Amino acid sequence: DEAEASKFVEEYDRTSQVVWNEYAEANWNYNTNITTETSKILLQKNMQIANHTLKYGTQARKFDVNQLQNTTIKRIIKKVQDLERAALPAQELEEYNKILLDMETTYSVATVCHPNGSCLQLEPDLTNVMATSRKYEDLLWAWEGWRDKAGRAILQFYPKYVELINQAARLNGYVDAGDSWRSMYETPSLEQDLERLFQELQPLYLNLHAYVRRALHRHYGAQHINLEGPIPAHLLGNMWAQTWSNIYDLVVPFPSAPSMDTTEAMLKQGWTPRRMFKEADDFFTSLGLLPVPPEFWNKSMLEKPTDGREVVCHASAWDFYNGKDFRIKQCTTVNLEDLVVAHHEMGHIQYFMQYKDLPVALRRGANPGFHEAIGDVLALSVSTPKHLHSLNLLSSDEHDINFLMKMALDKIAFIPFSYLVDQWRWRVFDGSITKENYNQEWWSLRLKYQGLCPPVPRTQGDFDPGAKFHIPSSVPYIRYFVSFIIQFQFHEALCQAAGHTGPLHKCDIYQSKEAGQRLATAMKLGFSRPWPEAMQLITGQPNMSASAMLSYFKPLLDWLRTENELHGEKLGWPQYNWTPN
Ligand SMILES: *[C@@H]1O[C@H](CO)[C@@H](O[C@@H]2O[C@H](CO)[C@@H](O[C@@H]3O[C@H](CO)[C@@H](O)[C@H](O)[C@@H]3O)[C@H](O)[C@H]2NC(C)=O)[C@H](O)[C@H]1NC(C)=O
Ligand SMILES: [Cl-]
Ligand SMILES: [Cl-]
Ligand SMILES: [Zn+2]
């Protein structure tokens, strides 16, 4: 009956708040202080939260969701029936929790050392080398070295991780873990929807690829770049070649129109990692959206500590399911790239504050992609020359194509990589890719989608996916692909609401209450309604669409077509078999 069902939801909500609150603190202390004490406290708080999940998930399965009128009640109960890892028998649950902890630690503490000297960490050392070095062999030292230490050591944990995470999914009614992850979007046509979105950005990516390949051919020499083959994976300014903005000096369309060194501008004018978040806080409030509580500033780790303690550096935002406690954990470097990431993480916090009045089971994004997109939308406005100049970090047709090129190196280059990652994982989860095919099938997709090849031939024992944070940390990736598509849809819609006329890329939504109002009401929905409703609240239409992204970059697509045609470039990589000598 309906009456017992709403009572159960109320009971679940109160008990979840307390137990979810306790787990968050226990997880925080490990993430901000990797030791042995905090690790086993987390392993024991894992059993406490699993008891709650098992207890209430059993009760939920005794409810026939099928016989329930109120859809909000119907929705929550259906979610509680999913136990996740808690569905596993005790021995396998503790094994699975240990493996995850082992993988997360292995990744976070891994270092790449010189013959008998300095040992380098991923952030900021190896990140800095990948971004600034222009020597082929030095970049290779960092690229290979990171994969030799982080990737290779993850390989031992991964098959059993796949086995146990799939087992949990089967016990919760799914065929495998990929199926379980995809269900978060509540869209039966998701795979075909994502494929069509990817195909629509092919002409824009292939033109950026061909142009960047030409620029690399210019600098690294004809012997190391094949203008009809895939680009060596280590030359794009980033460890995973997911974003390419750091090789801007190598690709700048009009060097005739030069732009400020934005990193040294920040360091000189006295930009603290604290001021970087303070300015991101200002942008949100200018839209009429909520400020971060005083408690946020007291308890957040906005900078890498000098204790000598190990930490999880990857940027993340933290909801304590309290309605009062919200935190950010980030190893912030003072540069433009981390200012964007600071806005991204503040977007998560805003989403937390907007739906804190909802039940905890519904305290979630419309879909995971929505949660990632909020900060990135504001960052698009922050990234404009007009907003950056007003922050004294910069000082028109040539500057216009340059800016669009800068944005393309991040936004466009990430489309194929963000698509790639879960294309690999889903096939790993469903059995298409086994442990003897992990690395081979990873590079097949690197070639197929990104048009990248490894700089060094891959050997047995290589597990390059393990050198990317999200893989050993078991964090789904397709969200970022959705985010990059939809953030431009949000941008377009918020700019038309702001009354911005002219080219989309010159829009700055700063201080627009109309743009804030559309964001607010959509975020307030949380996970109460299917995402097409939240999409419609912001954009006036319910579909994911690549139109807004192509509109934004339309001036660049025309310029690239002309430029690549006059060089007689071949779009794509007809010689997919090509690897370096
Ligand atoms: C199914 O059950 C759900 C949850 O019990 C009902 O949703 C609730 O609906 C009421 C309005 O009927 C919402 O109350 C509102 O609160 C705000 C306070 O900020 C106030 O300004 C409004 O005037 C209103 O009173 C309440 O938020 C909402 N709760 C949730 C969790 O969504 C729903 O009405 C039920 N559906 C049917 C068809 O009976
Ligand atoms: Cl890789
Ligand atoms: Cl996701
Ligand atoms: Zn995020």
Image (spheres, rainbow, N blue to C red):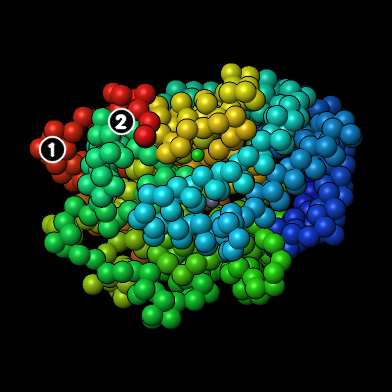
Q: Which residue is mark 1?
A: 567
Crowd band around label 2 with a 10 angstrom C-alpha radius: few (<14), some (14–19), many (20+): many
Rendered-image quadrant of the N terminus: top right
The image position of residue 185, as x and y in percent, is 55, 33
* Camera-nearest label, 2 or 1: 2
Question: In percent of the image, x 35 and y 55: which residue is there?
Answer: 134
Question: Of marks 2 and 1, which one's residue comes earlier in the chain?
Answer: 2
Mark 2: which amino acid? Gly
- Up-down: is 380 above or below 432? below
Name the outermost residue toward the front.
116
Q: Quadrant of residue 55?
A: top right
Crowd band around label 1 with a 10 angstrom C-alpha radius: few (<14), some (14–19), many (20+): few
Mark 1: which amino acid? His
Query: Regarding mark 2 in the picture, which secondary structure is present there?
Result: loop
Q: Indicate which disc residue 229 carries.
A: 2
Q: Are marks 2 and 1 in contact (CB under 8 Å)?
A: no
Rendered-image quadrant of the C terminus: top left
The residues bearing labels 2 and 1 have C-alpha atoms spaced at a distance of 16 Å
- Up-down: is 437 above or below 97? above
Question: In the rendered image, is residue 306 in sight?
Answer: yes
The image position of residue 428, as x and y in percent, is 61, 25
- Up-down: is 564 above or below 110? above
The image position of residue 292, as x and y in percent, is 57, 68
Question: In the rendered image, is residue 489 in sight?
Answer: no
Question: In percent of the image, x 23 and y 72: which residue is there?
Answer: 395
Closest to the observer, 536 or 446: 446
